[PDB]
Length: 168
Length: 168
Ligand SMILES: O=C(/C=C/c1ccc(O)c(O)c1)O[C@H](Cc1ccc(O)c(O)c1)C(=O)O
Image (cartoon, rainbow over all chains, first blue to last red; front, top):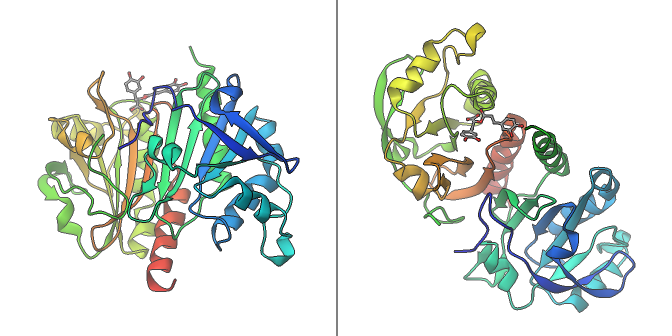
């Protein structure tokens, strides 16, 4: 199940995203060749654990930019849903303005390609993938729904892969 | 692809391990039902990223014991190779005495079952799996060969799954 394999090219995708400026744009994983990419899935918009994760990554996007690394979040919700959540203030339980793009995967094909579809519910597990500047998958993380991810740990991994990339 | 699926029983195994007392014993994942298990693969013995991880999990095994959690390491090397590394003095790059068992997977079937065999080389990637006290797989972590895992992160995940098990 899925085509995400360590040491092999990460599965490409082309999807509509809500961009940091608040507007829609169709983006592809291949747009970010030359940069490391952290690509993470969350189950659903308008939930309780996912916003804490999304906001944590968005708040700390600058730490990833200094590592020449693009962060991209994704769920199976529509792109309109993403925009409604961004336009809901954080004070009121929304995401607020974002520093990272949020991809919409409404046909669930990206989640299936990455092997993180919870088939009996049509939603993704908490999958996170680290892809190097050549597009090669370097790291797979999948959490069951109840437990969120750590930005600290993700930064540690990105830094460590970049460090070992310099060896010869 | 393997048979390790979030929310499903983690694949059972029965394999020879070198135990903390330095003796060989055949153990099974099902021996630890009723406790959380952290089951991690490392690629080969007598290497220079794996020992940092193994020694860290061994050194801090009491923190997992406080969480009622058993840590188990594994590689495709023979159990004789495992013990030779344990018996190598730490000052010469050895593991030293271990607080955790080290499973031998010489047929590569356990790595295949867990979807972490690097097929063109016959060794495992750095897979780590968190399995709950009912035997259900809760978390999947797979790193490419160059980059090690974090005990802190593993403890964070084990504790968080146990907390959400009780309330949520
Ligand atoms: O000993 C090492 C060191 C890996 C490493 C350490 C630093 C680097 O910058 C880098 O590119 C690779 O890895 C081995 C795993 C391994 C086994 C076989 C290989 O052909 C391999 O490339 C790595 C281990 O720790 O078990």
